[PDB]
Amino acid sequence: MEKLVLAGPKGRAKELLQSLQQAGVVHLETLRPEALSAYQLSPEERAELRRWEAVSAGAEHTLSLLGLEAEPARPFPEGLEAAEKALSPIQAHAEGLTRQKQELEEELALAQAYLEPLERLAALAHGLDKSPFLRVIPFLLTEKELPLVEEALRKALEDRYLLAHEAYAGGVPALVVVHRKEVDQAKAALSRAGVAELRLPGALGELPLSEAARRLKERAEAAPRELSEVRQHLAKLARESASTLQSLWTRAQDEVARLKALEELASGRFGFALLGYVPVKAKPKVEEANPPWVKPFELLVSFLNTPKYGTFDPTPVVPIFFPFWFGMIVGDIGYALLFYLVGRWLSGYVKRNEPLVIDLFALKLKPPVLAKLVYILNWMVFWTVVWGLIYGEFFGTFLEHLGVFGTPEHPGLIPILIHRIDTAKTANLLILLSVAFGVVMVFAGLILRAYLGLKHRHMAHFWEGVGYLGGLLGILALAASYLGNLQAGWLSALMYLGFGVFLLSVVMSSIWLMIPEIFTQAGHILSHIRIYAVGAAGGILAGLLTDVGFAMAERLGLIGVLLGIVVAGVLHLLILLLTTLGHMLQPIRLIWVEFFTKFGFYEENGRPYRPFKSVRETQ
Amino acid sequence: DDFAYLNARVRVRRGTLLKESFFQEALDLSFADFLRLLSETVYGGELAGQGLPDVDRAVLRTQAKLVGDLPRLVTGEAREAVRLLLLRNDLHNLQALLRAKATGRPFEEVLLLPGTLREEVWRQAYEAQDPAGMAQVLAVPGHPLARALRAVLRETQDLARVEALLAKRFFEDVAKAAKGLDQPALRDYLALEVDAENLRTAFKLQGSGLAPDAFFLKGGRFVDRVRFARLMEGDYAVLDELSGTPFSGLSGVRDLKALERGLRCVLLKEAKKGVQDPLGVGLVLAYVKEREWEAVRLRLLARRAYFGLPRAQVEEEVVC
Amino acid sequence: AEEAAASGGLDRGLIAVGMGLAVGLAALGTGVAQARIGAAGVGAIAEDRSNFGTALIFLLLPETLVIFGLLIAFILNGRL
Amino acid sequence: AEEAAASGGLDRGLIAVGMGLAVGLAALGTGVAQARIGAAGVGAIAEDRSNFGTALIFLLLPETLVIFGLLIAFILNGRL
Amino acid sequence: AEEAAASGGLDRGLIAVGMGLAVGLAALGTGVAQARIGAAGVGAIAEDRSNFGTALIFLLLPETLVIFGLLIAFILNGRL
Amino acid sequence: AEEAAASGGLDRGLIAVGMGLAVGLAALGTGVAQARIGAAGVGAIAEDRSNFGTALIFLLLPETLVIFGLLIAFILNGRL
Amino acid sequence: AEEAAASGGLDRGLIAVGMGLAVGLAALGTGVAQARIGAAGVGAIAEDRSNFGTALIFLLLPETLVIFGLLIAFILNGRL
Amino acid sequence: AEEAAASGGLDRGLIAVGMGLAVGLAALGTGVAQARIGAAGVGAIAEDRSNFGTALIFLLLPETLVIFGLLIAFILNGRL
Amino acid sequence: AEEAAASGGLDRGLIAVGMGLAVGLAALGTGVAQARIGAAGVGAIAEDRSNFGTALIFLLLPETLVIFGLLIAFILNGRL
Amino acid sequence: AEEAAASGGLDRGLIAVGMGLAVGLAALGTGVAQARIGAAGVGAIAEDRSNFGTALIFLLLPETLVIFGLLIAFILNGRL
């Protein structure tokens, strides 16, 4: 049989063992870390690992040069010998092509800059730059500097110096021509003004001007043609063999990871460890073992199966999000109506963007792999837009009517004149309807919170978690005495007094050394109420901006207003989007009050495992 | 002005700072394995050659783009506050530059990085042929280190003296400006920098027969003229009375190397607990000490590995 | 007051003065938070794209404050 | 009920100024308080993704003041 | 005020202005105390995860001020 | 009053005076916040010459508040 | 003003309106005074664990500022 | 904007006060917004002579608040 | 219209008060703005000792906002 | 005034508005002062334990101002 080595954590010893036991692997026996010692890699093993890293790196190097890097999930099993022989010709060829290319590009950059001055300068003293009798010194002057330089030279060098200049479109390249042995004096004069000698890089700088000028003119013409070719040969090599490198990269990487695995396990850096045996047949088999609701749930099953604390499933989160999330969309005239269209561009395809190619083949701004992952997300968006179109007629219950309100289904001048969601009675009930769901979520998090300390068997969490839920009851009690006054809520004016005893009476049994801090527990209650209220009311506000964007905001309303309002409407669209996206972050802002405060959830101030925001990114 | 964007830019950068556990790994490695490790880091990202000149250069160039680009990114009241920190790295360039003009030696073999004075200011200064002109070219970025230079240059043209009176006058200039830009975090640190300077001026010039009052400049915390005079006679019993300061750790120590090691570790510590004050200059303060100290340990660990020096000779100097 | 299609009245007018303070102040606080964070978000994406999502989430959060100040204001004036 | 009008009144206008202080001032303190936390939050996620939970809890925390202020304004203005 | 929900006197409107200030301003002060100390707490977690609590105890103290504003408003509008 | 109102007089005028406070304060918070970041932002544009745009978009974000608040005053001051 | 019950004379109203200025301005002052020491105060612990006590005892002193402002307000309000 | 009889009137005053506010307030926000960014940005051209074009496009983004306020102000209080 | 309260009574009174706010605020936002550019500008004259002309013109740019607010108010009350 | 019945005064109500200013501003100011010395005190322990006394003597001084303010308010209003 094949020997196989296993690791896991101490906490899941039994759950890991049961799963492995089932999977294919048989003869599972535990091993403590002292047993794992002395099975650290021999020097030969470390040399294979070093070499596997070179191949990994070496591909990253070749593949980056050649063009773009792409990491596939497709390796190609090969030897040490096979992978290194593959890599050596292409890296060599490509290294060589990129070097030419850099030299070609630097030469162009200098030649493009300095051809016109050197031409001018060479011309001025033509055939007198290679004479010993006369000395030439080139230098650049701006219009501003030219008088100063001339004065300085003239006093220094009398009237037996020659200052000539010729233009080039902007300043003047100037040449001063002086006798041999009058060089020091000539220089000294330039140095006092702050002007210094122009010399180019390499052989050209050192060559007579006439040679330097002829050659620069030649390099500017030649380079762009040769650059084109080198870039072409390099493109072909990527095109044909970018895959070869990518497949070496993946394979090489798998071997590096395997040998690293054995060095870690060997130093007794995994707490629960197993040894077992699999026949050759069993070896694959071990590795082997309404859409809105079902679809995200089947991917979440992978997190059902790995618990980490006294926590329960992270799955209650998704159906709390959905009603509240759909009800941020409530327009029906140029808000939800426009947004319908948006859905199709993410769940179909567009080419009206540049960084985004065709979505149907998985090509977006986001990385090509990430884009294939967020298909599910894009669907979950599509389901949100769809349901929002329905809750846009729910809103139009409170608008449209031919007798209850003073605005028809569609007036014949312009659709929508004045909104009729400005009735006082109508706004309050839609806010109070919304509040009721926030309350349901307060009970559900703290009831699980208690069950958490019961099955994690820390009484200090149980006791604190039970007590805080008493305060909700007081909070609601007190509200009723003010929402109904004494006409209603005189059925909770006496229970409230005792509701207050419950908040503190269980919490004190754990003692606790910050009694004030209970104020902040009451803060969390309050938020679920305010956020659901903001979710309705701020949602409704979204619609009331659309008054002046695709509704009467010109004349008294008339036929012309229909096609006149669209001036302001388009300008209004980007403004509208930004504030309504702000509301859609409320579901997650709500979730995190409870989730990261260990209300039947994994998190509690830090600790591995993602925020649900990132989970839902892909699901 | 303002540190609002700038602090934020640095907070992302504090993510790629080198933690203690890297230098821990690096000591166990040979030079070949060190080089593979180094390349993972951001200093590694400027690397250009396996050998020693190239390691010194990759380190320096990392400091040039991530730390020496900070004064440009702010202006005014922000800029003066950040600038004082940057100024110490500029003084190092200046003292070497002033020395290349004066003793006639090339531009080369000096420290160059951007900070407050750009690369071009140092080239135009180099090429200046009158010390007074050299000085106006330096005065262009604006800073207290000009104003400090300008007064010293009026008294003298002797190299050794300009160096000492510039440094003394410069920390005095720094202190007054810094006190006027407020914040408790900066004030505590400033006090330590001056106290450390005071001790250190006394050590470098030890036993030269000179005045001990010349080694004490205002900004102090617990140190005075008498401790300096005793110290100058060679007595280290003064450091054994020095507690209530974080230099409590210098007690019972009498080696110059252990003493000076001690001051650099203390200054590191103050700055590392200035992240409980990240508002304004506090965070930047912590960020500069850490980039500097980090860069220093990779250079010492690289030297230690290349020449096969003894481990304990460097294991102690790469931790505080 | 009212906000059905008009809000005319000397009495209502008094309510209008009262509410605009609350909008004012709530909007003022939003301005300091949203801008500072937005700049902070542009630095995060520029160094590391592994924090591009955090930068975006932070931007949205100060938007709730300005809407709160509008909603109270609407409420006292005839509701939504 | 709690905080509503439909007709306005001279009495209401003075009531409107008073309720307006609470939401307006609280949100100004929420905005600044968040803003500073928000700057520091760039740093929390950046050092480690094992303090990233902590940064989220800090950000939620200055909201309590504004929520509290909505509540005082509704209560005072809807108790008999 | 103690009596205000949909109508009330001119007089009642005036107590509502004055008392309104006291709470609103506490929220304001809480937020300024929170801004500085909160921002400092983000440094502490970043360095060491385990001493999130120290930051929290120092922070718990300005909450007391918001609660103090509430009580001034409560007593002066009308005693319980 | 406005060209989309047809109610003027003393009555519209109190509302216009009073509601005017809100936009002015929304502009103040927006103002102070846009300016600080924008200055630091010059360095951003300076660095990113191909991603210069990012800096431009972050500036636009505080403006969103001022303009949104004008539109709210427009509804309130004329809806016919 | 009145302590128990809401104000019912214009004079009682006017006093309430003035007295508010003292508890508001104080309330704000307790807030600012806490923040500089409070933010540092974490630092106290950090530097020296033993002298965590020294930071707290300073923070406590601004709490005094609000109670002194309340006492004047509590007495003065009841009668004209 | 204009003064006349047909861009003038008593009727026009009620419009004029509201619309006048719109330029003032837009002006307020613009001055502070524009100042820091413009202070730093002119400075850049002084230092680096390749940022001048960038500085000019950048400068107009805070100018946008006054230009916006101005369009509202002008049209509504135009002729008729 | 003009600023009066006896050449149009109560209707007029509102215009006069509201218009004063546009000018007053125009003046505040400009005033502070001038300071920022002035402060930065010092650097520019020290750095480039012949680019005196650049500092003076940058400074001029906030003055534009007071000439804008102060005239608008003036034209409108100039009708009568 | 008293909370009990034994005061009345038309004059006194006006005195309450004016006096609310003096207490409130003195507590604001005393607090801001207090904080600087308290942050400074953090430094004082850090520098030297023995001269905790120095922090103490300076720190007494802003207290005098609020205390003085409380007595002034009682004399002007509440003496009877």
Image (cartoon, coloured by chain):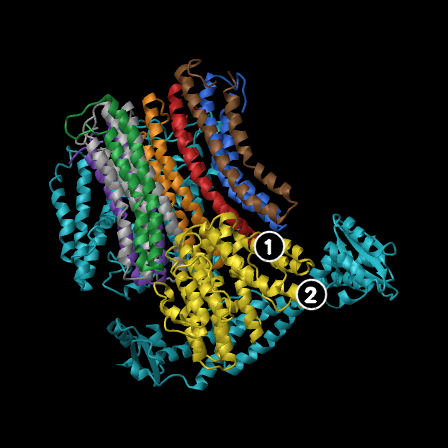
Chain colours: A cyan, B yellow, C orange, E purple, F red, H blue, I brown, J green
User: Marks 1 and 2, Cα distance to the nearest angstrom?
Assistant: 47 Å
Q: Please give the name of the residue rendered at 83% of the width and 54% of the height, measured from the top-left corner.
A: A163
Mark 1 highlights which residue? B150
Measured from the top left, where is residue B41 in percent x and y?
48, 68
Instruction: Inspect this view and state whether residue B169 appears.
Output: yes
Above or below, comparing residue A470 to residue F69 in the picture: below
Q: Element at badge 2? A: helix
- The quadrant of the picture occupied by the C terminus of chain A is bottom left
Determine the image quadrant of residue A536. Answer: top left
Q: Please give the name of the residue rendered at 46% of the width and 82% of the height, measured from the top-left corner.
A: B310
Mark 2 highlights which residue? A104
Q: Please give the name of the residue rendered at 52% of the width and 26% of the height, measured from the top-left corner.
A: I72
> How would you rate the neighbour count of disc 2 (Cα within 10 Å): few for under 14, some for 14-19, many for 20 or more?
some
Select label 1 or label 2 by which is in front: 1
Above or below, comparing residue H48 to residue A133 in the picture: above
> How would you rate the neighbour count of disc 1 (Cα within 10 Å): few for under 14, some for 14-19, many for 20 or more?
some
